[PDB]
Image 1 (tube, one colour):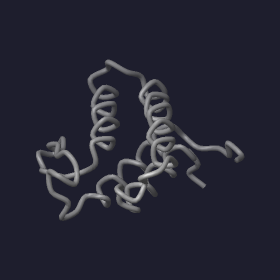
Image 2 (tube, rainbow, N blue to C red):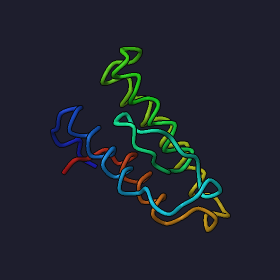
Image 3 (tube, rainbow, N blue to C red):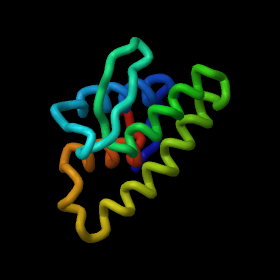
Length: 108
């Protein structure tokens, strides 16, 4: 897939919005919950939480914009790999779609 052309912020923003939309009636069993920077309680898969923390680092200054993006891509591939394996039915299709977009990092 062509790399195309986009800013780091635009790509990061695209995935963040998807995560927010992904939030739903899903309870603790469905996944873990984290407090939004705005102070809004949201629910997302444990994997979503992992990248969420990475985002915070970009703000904290612990990680760079590209470093945070890079970290998300590597873990995204691992998550996608597990999804590809069997017993993928256990995971929700909506969550699978999110991982696919992250791995295929194309703003388009």
